[PDB]
Amino acid sequence: EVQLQQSGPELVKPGASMKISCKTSGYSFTGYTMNWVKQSHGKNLEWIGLINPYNGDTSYNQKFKGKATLTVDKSSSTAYMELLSLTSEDSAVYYCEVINTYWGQGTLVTVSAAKTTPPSVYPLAPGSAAQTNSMVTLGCLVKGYFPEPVTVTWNSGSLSSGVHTFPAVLQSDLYTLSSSVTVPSSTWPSETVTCNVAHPASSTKVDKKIVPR
Amino acid sequence: EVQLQQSGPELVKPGASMKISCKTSGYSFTGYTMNWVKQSHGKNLEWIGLINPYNGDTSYNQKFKGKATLTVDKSSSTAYMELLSLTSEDSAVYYCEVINTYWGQGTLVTVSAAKTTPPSVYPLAPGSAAQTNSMVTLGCLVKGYFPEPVTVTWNSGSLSSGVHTFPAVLQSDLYTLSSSVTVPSSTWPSETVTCNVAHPASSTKVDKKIVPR
Amino acid sequence: IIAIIKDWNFAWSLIFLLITIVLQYGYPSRSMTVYVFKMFVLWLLWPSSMALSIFSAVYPIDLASQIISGIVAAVSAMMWISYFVQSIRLFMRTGSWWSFNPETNCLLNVPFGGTIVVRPLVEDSTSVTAVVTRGHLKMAGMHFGACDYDRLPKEVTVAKPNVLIYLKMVKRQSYGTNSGVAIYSRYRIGNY
Amino acid sequence: AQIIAIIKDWNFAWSLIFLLITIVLQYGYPSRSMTVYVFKMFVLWLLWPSSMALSIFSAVYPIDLASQIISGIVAAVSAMMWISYFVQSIRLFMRTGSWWSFNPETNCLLNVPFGGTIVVRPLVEDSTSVTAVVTRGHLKMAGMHFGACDYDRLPKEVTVAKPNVLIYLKMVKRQSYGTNSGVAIYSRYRIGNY
Amino acid sequence: DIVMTQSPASLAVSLGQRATISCKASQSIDYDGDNYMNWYQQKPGQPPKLLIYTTSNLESGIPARFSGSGSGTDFTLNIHPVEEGDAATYYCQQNNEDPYTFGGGTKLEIKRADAAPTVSIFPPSSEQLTSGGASVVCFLNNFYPKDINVKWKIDGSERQNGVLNSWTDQDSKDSTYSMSSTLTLTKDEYERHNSYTCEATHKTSTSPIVKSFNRNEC
Amino acid sequence: DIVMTQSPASLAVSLGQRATISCKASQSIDYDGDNYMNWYQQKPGQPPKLLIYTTSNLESGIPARFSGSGSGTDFTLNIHPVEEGDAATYYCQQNNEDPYTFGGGTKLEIKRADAAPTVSIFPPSSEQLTSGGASVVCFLNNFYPKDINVKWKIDGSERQNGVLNSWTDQDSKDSTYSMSSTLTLTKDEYERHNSYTCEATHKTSTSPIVKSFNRNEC
């Protein structure tokens, strides 16, 4: 089973240097050429470069020659990409692959002159809705966090079906996200659901049980 | 799509010579290897010989050095084994095979001094049963025919279930056979029930409907 | 005299040029059916080496050169006798001229298009492998002409000097438009 | 007076050389991995310059002017293929730092990721697909010995190195026979022209 | 040559039970490390179907119930689940020597719980009586096992002359037997007797089932 | 150096119908005798998955619904049996020359039947009121198609300031859209008015569905 786990999301200053660690497992590490690809804002893929692990020989894109450097560590069975002198046109998702089939999980890199803000989640409840139909919607609002991403789940992963995670919106250099799950009217408000919101930039793994209204 | 078809049943006199055909189809005939197998008395499988369709390369058995010849006709894709000195021990079934998988239908040869007698079928009736259920057993009996086999079927092969056909019994150099089907009450005697026999040696197609007394 | 050694030098340079052409091409170029080149050069070079070793033994510089020329004459005689024995033993059984290959103990017969194709196979395991790549078939490293993947035989033969071994199509697969792989295994051996 | 001595020396040397070629045309073309291979390497390497020297010797003491023309043509084309071999071999050694680039048969190498290392062997049977067979802990690729590889740890990507390009080959389809043997193929993807 | 005497001759196993056919050899059939021994399955009225190639490998399109391997000079074919559709005969071979000798015979018969024979009389009529000879049968159907003794009780005292008993093979859908007990009589013998009775002694039935036909009531 | 453009921008293909994606390049991608264009599929939030290697071949585990054709300069990815798990973004890569230029990307979404959104109105929570603000939202549930207008009204007066709309991507199980229409308010703006109207008009109907709420009734 070929797996290529990456490091995780990172926020960096506009002009610093940082390193993505693509850690592999399963195969004989020295011998499969590792290829690094960058996916820009929205949907636009750009090739960064390949590197042989055993030989150490590299090959770079023309636009990325000197912008990023590829290194191999055989003992930890890892590869690294160093990005230097980060600018505003570098906020992108970076993938590592081997035989163009087994890709990486994806590392989201944010480049901004801002700070990490824990989210102020405000769970919204319909007060005196009196919905006769038994698919009443219940949701939570996440306001005031930076940067991406934030993981929101329902009943700590027990409520799998009926989820609706929405893309974030940006205003005043701040991110706002909302969620909504239709629930049967017999459960609400007798049963207890939790809008589990976790922000890896601030480690604010709050449970945030919804208050009925 | 590989299919080998043989000739059919044959009665031969002692001292004669019977030629067994094997018309292959569905493949490039020249390049495989035909192989002949003799089955005697029900459970005795013996080997005779193989022959390349390309060359005349044969390899016979030690008990079939002068009792069998193998021939290949490369115009209609036919193997053409003929037999020599057909004694009383040669009443047997003969099979082609190619790669030990695609076998033939089996040619039955009988060595006897008799005639190809018509089947004297006597379809009789139950006498005053006065009780017809959904599993009422009715039978057709045929006596006095030679040689094997008879293609005994009911109503031109429509009754493919619940039919019990019996092996031939030999007495006074004669063959007796019987068959029974469990017919429902709705098809007897409201529907046409006919026992059909077929002797390929006598070249007859006599079929008779069973009529109660 | 004088002109004789000039003709000898010209003949030696010319025949070394044909040895040059036959060694670098024919077998290790794309492995087509021009193996008669190596056959005709080897049939020229066996009695040539015999004659040169005999002429060096007849007029020796010393005793060591005489015994070395006698040793290489005996070695060339031994290898020629071994080649003739191993090639004659494979010609009374199979009617194919590919038994006259310089080192061959098996012959692979593959039927397609209504004809069998015989190639001087070098060594087979208990399960040979067919590879079809576009309109071309390669079986145990030998170029078996052009043959489609769907029209691949389910039975091939290999003719050892003491036995005939029948291989049947055990496994098959296709990956391209008409390219694929196949695995043949023995099911029945025939004693010659 | 000393013509007989140089004639005997020439006869002895060419008898030894004709023995050395004879154990290369036979006994050396089937066995292409370990045995009867140093003899083949020596013969195939000194084949071109000895032919060039023979044409030079024929041109130095010639017979006719047409003999001079054809001997100069033969020497020029022999030097041309020897120079082309040294150019292609130096290019292949510069692109891939292995001694196996210096063989005179082919200018293409096959690199296989075996056991944490990369094993490089010359590849004469070059095509779109490269086959690989296993012999229960013994693997052969394109008729070449490649160590003692198993089947469950088969490499999923091999490379071939040429003087111009480097061609990657991924394992497309495999089939297993026996307890530990198997046969896999490798088809081309992503040629890289550095 | 090669002499193969397989030790079983008639196996009676059930669905879910273990079937094992042990086949032997006179000497070694080894060539190049491979012992060539084929296994075939033949149904009645059908050509043999190849089950097993060189001792271990499987026919393409055959199920994996038959995969007993064996080695040396002991070759066993094992059917571990045993489906209902398996009433056939299994044969050895050797694809090694010159004669290619086959094996003996092993009739594998599927076990099913004991069912009473369906006795149904089939009285004679005027057609074969006008032909010259009458035939009377018992027609015992769907019984277990073959050790059922039929008996004729014509006109009182028993008759044990001119009797032909015919068995059948195992059925491929429900695995039952069938009987045909023919008695052939002349015209005067059929006219001289009226009370034709048929009985069958069976191990499942505590008493013989009595079925009779009489001529005068027709 | 290699400029690659894809002619379709967005697709509208139902279940079982042909979907063609054309990725015309400008240089020659063929090396030796094989074109090297890889075809990739990416679901939202996931890395791309390789479908087609050398313009014709298929990934092991990728079904035969996707086919590759074309040669030289023009290339086409074709799907006859378009299934429910198909709405994604498809890319082309040269895999021949040095920069390995990816394609522009074609977004394929499965055409669905028209549906009415289940609009729900949410009063703002007391935590936001204690924090010193307000934010009313509307969670429009599963509808189709994309074009739908949402108006926010404050006691009969339309407010064009602070209205934000966020659309989720199309579902991979039933191809349905959902929307969040939010409106942020301060303390004085929330205390000034009481009746907030969340109007939503969709082209599948005529009358917009009214989900107006009041502070006294909530």
Image (tube, coloured by chain):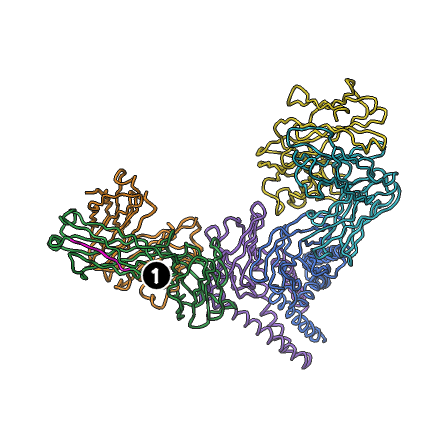
Chain colours: A cyan, B orange, C purple, D blue, E green, F yellow
x then y, percent, for residue B23:
36, 51
Above or below for F37 versus D144: above
Quadrant of the frame with the N terminus of chain E: bottom left
**First to last magenta residue range:** E195-201
Is residue F74 in sight in this rendering?
no
Where does the image place residue A149, in percent across and percent down from the top left?
78, 41
Residue on which disc 1 sits: B38
- Determine whether, in the image, residue C93 is placed left or right of residue D66: left
For this orientation, the residue located farthest to the top is F156
Q: Amino acid at mark 1?
A: Lys
Q: Residue furthest bottom?
A: C63
Residue nearest the viewer, comparing B134 with F191: F191
Q: Quadrant of residue C11?
A: bottom right
Tell which subunit mark 1 falls on. B
Q: Quadrant of residue D14?
A: bottom right
Instruction: Tell me: E54 left or right of D166.
Output: left
Count of numbered labels shown in the rendering: 1
Residue F170 percent across, percent down from the top left: 67, 34
